[PDB]
Amino acid sequence: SQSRTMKLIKDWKDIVNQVGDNRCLLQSLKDSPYYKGFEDKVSIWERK
Amino acid sequence: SQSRTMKLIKDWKDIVNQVGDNRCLLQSLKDSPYYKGFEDKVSIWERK
């Protein structure tokens, strides 16, 4: 109403759906038998 | 004294000095200007 200007943020679903895809992709990586040698990077991206 | 047998562990300094070398090596990596793109693996090895 009074004259200010802020950078509001739109298109949220585009951002959130990528995050959901990445988390279910990590769950898909959790079923691999070679997960025991790569678990430590998965922990990073999990918490991130 | 009574007859048992356990695998006791010797040569400790050989193991510990490698750990000290690795921690001071990480500190040497902490002075690099390109540390901002590789900080996340350094956090892993730091806590480990």
Image: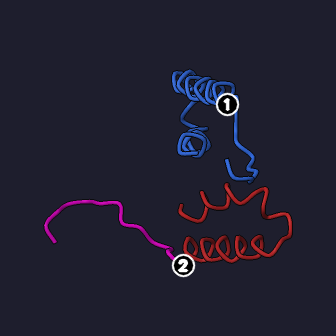
Chain colours: A red, B blue
Residue B20, position as x, y percentages in the image: 58, 26
Relative placement, left or right, of A9 versus B2 is: left
Q: Tell me the residue at 63%/25% (across/down).
A: B13
Is the stretch drawn in magenta largely helix, strand or loop?
A: loop
| Chain ID of residue with mark 1 | B
Q: Is residue B29 above or below residue A21?
A: above
Q: Which of the 4 image quarters holds residue B45? A: top right
Residue B46 within the segment the image draws in magenta: no
Q: Say what amino acid the circle numbered 2 marks.
A: Lys
Relative placement, left or right, of A25 versus B32 is: right
The residue that label 1 is drawn on is B15
Residue A43, position as x, y percentages in the image: 62, 61
- Classify mark 2: helix, strand or loop: helix
The residue that label 2 is drawn on is A13
Which of the pair B38/A6 is nearer the observer? B38
Labels 1, 2: front one: 1
Q: Which of the 4 image quarters holds residue A24? A: bottom right
Q: Is residue B1 above or below residue B35?
A: below
- Classify mark 1: helix, strand or loop: helix
| Chain ID of residue with mark 2 | A
Residue A6, position as x, y percentages in the image: 29, 60
Q: Is residue B43 above or below residue A31?
A: above
Q: Give the residue at the far right of this rendering.
A: A33
Stretch of the chain drawn in magenta: A1-12
> Are marks 1 and 2 in one subunit?
no
Residue B5, position as x, y percentages in the image: 76, 51
Report how far apart the C-alphas of labels 1 and 2 lie in the structure.
51 Å
Relative placement, left or right, of B25 versus B10 is: left
